[PDB]
Image (cartoon, rainbow, N blue to C red):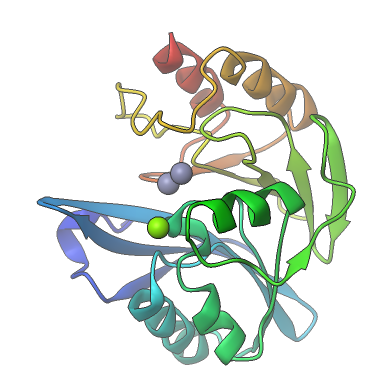
Length: 226
Ligand SMILES: [Mg+2]
Ligand SMILES: [Zn+2]
Ligand SMILES: [Zn+2]
């Protein structure tokens, strides 16, 4: 039932119910010859929605908003981007066009600027050192340390025990580390442990790319990082 690269053309988006008031969004994108899939999150708060990550580009993010408005029928009022790469901030200008208040960590804004990528407008201050946590509407935003990138954050929804691990967590089938050009492989194991120790009751763990699983995904990531 979970969408993969094989059932979504580039330029379409799909939503998938994870629990009460929680969906993942799934999109696709081609770099050169390779097509990938990518996951974000949608969390209901009263009569509004908080978006976690873009759908990897402006065309995908417009379609994300259209799918959200079809399937759910509530406005996206704020967004959070979980690191600086295009699959997280790519399409932030689409969000701003639509009146969305876009947030990320200060480091993510600096790194995104340095990479020539779109930059969320507002900083989540108080997310500066490994271990920092802030509450944000219906979720916690946790900065566990460097791993996939120096700035990567995870988002936990406590009501329903859902952890969006983003690109710091690999899916079950993935056996290679991936894009490690911004990675901190030395620190990635300690970062994962901080996540495991913080969210031991998580029922679902969603990676940045691929299929969701449980908490087994965290140690699987430590194994893949070697
Ligand atoms: Mg870019
Ligand atoms: Zn990335
Ligand atoms: Zn990614």
